[PDB]
Image: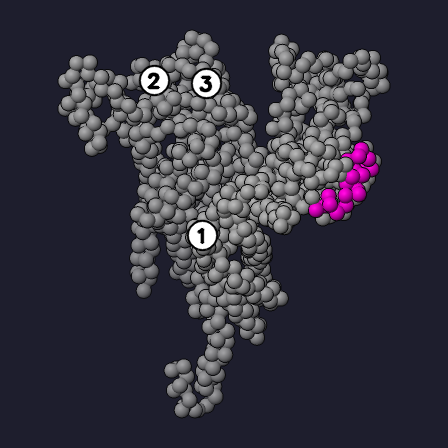
Amino acid sequence: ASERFKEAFRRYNYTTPKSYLELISLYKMLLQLKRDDLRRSKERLENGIDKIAQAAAQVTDLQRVLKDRTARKAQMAERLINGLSGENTRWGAEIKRLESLEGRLVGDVLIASAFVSYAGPFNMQFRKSLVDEKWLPDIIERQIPMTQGIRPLDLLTDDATKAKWANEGLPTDPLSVENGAIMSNASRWALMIDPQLQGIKWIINKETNNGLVIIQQSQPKYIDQVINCIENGWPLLIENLPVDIDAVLDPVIGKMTIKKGRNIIMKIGDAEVQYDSRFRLYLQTKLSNPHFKPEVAAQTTLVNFCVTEKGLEDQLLALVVDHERPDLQEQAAGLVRSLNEYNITLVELENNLLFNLANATGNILENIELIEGLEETKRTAVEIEEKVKLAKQTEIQIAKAREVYRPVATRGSLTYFLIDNLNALDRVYHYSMANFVFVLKKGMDMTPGGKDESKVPLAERLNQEVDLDKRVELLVETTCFVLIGYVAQGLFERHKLIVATQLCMQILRSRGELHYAKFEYLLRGPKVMGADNPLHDWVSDSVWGSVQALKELDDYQGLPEDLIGSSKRWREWMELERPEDEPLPGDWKRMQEFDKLLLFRALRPDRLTSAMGRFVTNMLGAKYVTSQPYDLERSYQDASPGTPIFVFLSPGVDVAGSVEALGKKL
Amino acid sequence: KLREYNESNAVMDLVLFQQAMEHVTRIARIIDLPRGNAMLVGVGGSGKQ
Amino acid sequence: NQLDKKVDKLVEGAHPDFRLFLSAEPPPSLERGLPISLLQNSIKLTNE
Amino acid sequence: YQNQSKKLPKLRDWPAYNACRKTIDDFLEMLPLFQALTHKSMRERHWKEVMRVTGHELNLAEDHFKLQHEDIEDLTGAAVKEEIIEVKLNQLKADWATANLALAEYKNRGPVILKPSDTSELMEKLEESQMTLGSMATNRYSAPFRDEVQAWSIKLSTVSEIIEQWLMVQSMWQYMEAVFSGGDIVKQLPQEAKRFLNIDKNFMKIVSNALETQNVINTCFGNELMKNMLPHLHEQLEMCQKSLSAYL
């Protein structure tokens, strides 16, 4: 896996014994802990069994002795015995759950151990391919007892726990929740490759009030505040440790060498005298691609958090879903974190009936607090029953809405990934991902076709169709439209068509592709040695070679046939004639139906540029390179103060007086 | 005498697997050599120490 | 950094009638200049 | 049946004889239950049947006979139709998992080229099955299977069209191969002859991505045949032959 990864993605993993020993450590941890947990669960029902048995024996003694007052005695006896049964039922039932889990423990914890131990350094695809297609099959082969509908993601954390986590800023893709469970059970705590702040977000919203000592490797006091967190258990936050190479932290935080690992420490201690670490460290690497030595990487762990296409798609898809389906969202959110008291109520009223039993200790038809404590304990079962199924159907609606907005959100996400990589060119375009998503909310939310507001400076909006399908196929466009608009607010008309060209290219690459044959032609220079076949005002001598090269293309090889055929018009064309609506007559452009790009690339530059403009406007409306109206109020006070107002200045223009009047206008 | 190198310099642990002892025996040959540079070429983090 | 480091909280705590206005000629786009985080989070304008 | 078989010779007063009528009442609706427990009906459809036949006594996943035993017959008919379309899709998916190729070696250098196979078999096995798919689309009971039909139908159509375009490429590539086999075929336009090497290499790569891809669907979907180099080689085929005729 490391091999085909590294020779797929330049990021480098180095294996060691200490990893295999680490897996031993982690598995032994989890197995023994879960065994203790199930143990400390089991006692409850067990104990009450004995008193139930004794009380039932005593009442049966009553009836065997019996062979009007007796009738009422009997009625209390009936309700009592039925209640005692109905209680001890779920008692033994839960205990047998506990032992079934006990049986599955070995294999299930094996899968979870391997999963959460080494799934971190690889992509979702590698993670799935490794686990579900090698080791789960291998656990089928050797057949260690384990349940096969296994999600080890739901083996370090719970939907309530993850619900808080996402509420504390954990992103919604499987990647983020997986990594969150990972650091919730990390033991060499993994280096968190987060060049987008989102892991830092979940940490700071979730893991700060303990006293989050955030600090970087820039001082010798850094060791001393490590001792402070040792003496204080503080979460020390590292920000991009791999900005250097340093040689003191490995004893400090490395958990140096493992054989079977039953011996990890996470906090303050008593026999600890070296004072290396007595606190649970946090790290945040803002570098997307670190590198470390095989020795160096050997002593600590690593986990992915670089935003990808699907991850960003999922975050923003969740945003649009709960933005347009907030109701089932809040139903789910309330129930998932109210189930705690729902369960506590029934188990504790059961406990009250149990202590009513503890007060019996010698009377049954006379310790009648049992009947009272029995009835409510009975119908406290009703509380939890409908919650689970409503949760499941709500999750069904969530998956439904996920896929419904998946095309729309995927197009918008695509366009984001575009502008992300487009930021490689610098000052013509630099916005924040926050500013981005704000434009996104502008496109989905203030979408006067998402609402009924026809009284807007947005008539492209439906303005009358709040209906959700019109909203689908409107807001899908409104997002990307306001995107390219406010992007253009910092763009030059010199490059807006550059933007348009690759926008159309990547849109078709989403819904197909222009092949590396066609597209690599479109890039690499269009010329081979000249062809004397074009003669000679048909085609220029350099264009002779251009045509000759283009006569190899399966979409373009038929060219000299066309030359000999309509020699008249092709002589006409490259004799510097410029029709532009139908520059060349579409006869060959239906004899080719070419990809809108490659023909003039061999032939005609000016009509090529006009054709790029026309084609883009066909896809994207006429408004692409059409310049920005130099606003004063809206595109500035539509946004927040927290996004300050700045301007790029062309030579010989000032908005300072315009800023003043703008003030005086408002 | 496992404890005796389990009480030795900063370990880069490998407890007994066959190949390890075969390497160790090669070196135990090699150590009795002037300039006895047994250059244990391999990956760090594994067993050399 | 000596103004934006303040911005990152102050304009987020700013009284909601605060309109701060900045203006700069952009130097050459790879010659020595301005960090990105400056205009990642500010409103912009082109002029011709 | 054994229980009833001995009530046949007995006959006395009707208030006693009521057991005969109730016993025979059991059988008449037993056969719909016979079909209902034939696993061919998937239990969600049977679950709706429970919702309809007032068999709510079986809302539990456990269906004991005290709970197990007009509207029943028609729903069992729909379950039978379920079974029928299940059968219709079974051999299709199985046999098209068993898709396989046939590559007759060409004379020089023995490259195994697909010409016992691009015979009408690999197209018509797709096409008659596609008419079957269209029929079950017009059969009211492929409704779940309709989307398997969509995915398959698209795969089959693509594969057939790929076979067609590939065989045209192969045919004219053979012709130029049978023209540019070597030697004096190069003494006038090495321009054309230089591409012959790499395009023969391309034919070899296709021979490969048919050899390892021993499923017709996944040969057409095979490596680099989900890559439209076939049009490029097709243009190479068409371009050189007209110049050859010109020199002729």
Q: Which color scheme does this rendered protein use?
A: one colour
Could you tell me which chain the residue with mark 3 belongs to?
A
Left or right placement of residue D221 versus residue A267 in this view: right
- Residue at (38, 87) in percent of width and height: D6
Observer able to see residue A477: no
Give the residue number, with chain letter if any, for mark 2.
Answer: A251
Where in the figure is residue A211, as x and y percent of width and height?
A: 48, 18
Instruction: Name the mark nearer the viewer: 3 or 1.
Output: 1
The label on residue A52 is: none
Could you tell me how far apart the alpha carbons at marks 3 and 1 are, in whole angstroms?
A: 63 Å
Residue A345 against residue A277 in the figure, above or below:
below
Position above or below: A445 against D247: above
Left or right, residue A124 beside residue A105: right
Disc 3 to disc 2, C-alpha distance: 15 Å
Where does the magenta region start and end?
Answer: A561-580
Q: Residues within 10 Å of mark 2 (few under 14, many from 20)?
A: few
Q: Which residue is mark 1?
A: D108
Amino acid at dot 3: Leu
Q: Nearer the viewer, residue A432 or A34?
A: A432
Q: Earlier in the sequence, mark 3 or mark 2?
A: 3
Q: Main secondary structure of the magenta part?
A: helix
Mark 2 or mark 1: which is in front? 1
Does dot 1 land on a helix, a strand or a loop?
loop
> In the rendered structure, the residue with mark 2 lies on which chain?
A
Q: Secondary structure at mark 2?
A: helix
> How far, Cα to Cα, is label 2 from label 1?
68 Å
Task: Give the residue displayed 33% in from the left and 33% down from the top.
Answer: A23
**Residue, disc 3:** A241
Residue A574 is one of the magenta-drawn residues: yes
Q: Amino acid at mark 2?
A: Pro
Label 1 is placed on what type of residue? Answer: Asn
